[PDB]
Image (cartoon, rainbow over all chains, first blue to last red; front, side, top):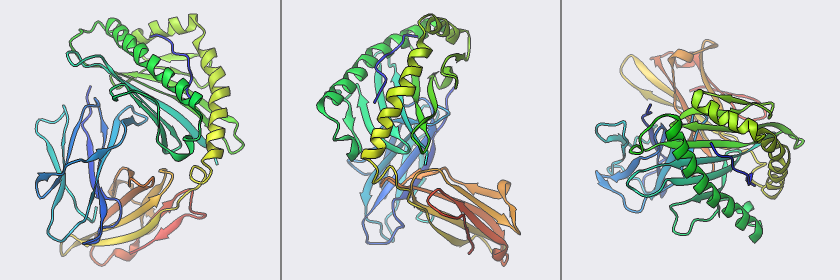
Length: 9
Length: 99
Length: 274
């Protein structure tokens, strides 16, 4: 299962 | 800033004339990801060749497997033809059943 | 033994040819189990191994939503990278990410990863402590400052110590027929005369899983590192892998050479000769 939080560059 | 593909052409199982098998062209170590690969039988393109999903190695370089069913014979010649931004001309690697 | 789960993202801009393409693939060990492609006709997370097919509809909806959000997020990241490197909007560029976890035989976290590249070069990576970052250049230092301010490392750590290992443990159980089976190499030596004076000995390993393997040649018991041609391990297409190693030897001297094979499916390393 993937991590559902993305963080912008 | 770019990396040229390594190319191997080989069969899934040891080749035996008249027995069905899979012809594989494995391209790896390249960057960027755009690449064109044809499988050739007697110099002509084999239709409906399939390929794997784009993935990459620890050094970030990409790899792909192109493959098709084939029945090798004594006289039929097979090859892989690869184009990539790093190549001034397409590179042809002939299938050798011993490699 | 030990096991790994990894997700691999590739985001590729292509000015004049639409918006950047976003791809994800997921692996357990050397087994692909899921994929996503924004260029697909109806982009969704799709199963690629039989043991993931039993995950319910909520799993697939959540995984697809993550990937659809990522398509947009990574298009923004590509625009940001152009700014950070003073680059033109005319060129094509690539962001890559690999993240995931390794577990030991008891299922406990051995280590976690979250690392990124821009145009094929390292950009930023979570350190093994799961609490700090290594930035490759002053551009990535801008990202690092943002991620420190937002405590991104702590959020990654909570995932890597929790859901990452928990889901990998479940996949290993559901896929125990394949993910927990090593297939040992089938090995043999072939002999190819080159001339009157020399012959190629080629040591073959076929049909093995996982991909990790060691193949070496020795002459009189001494490793032949500089004199061995070793091809990259390559996929057969049936889940298994292939590799060979070759040496050029003087005619008549074949018996001085031995091939040595190490693989986790072999209870003891193998020695072969022509």
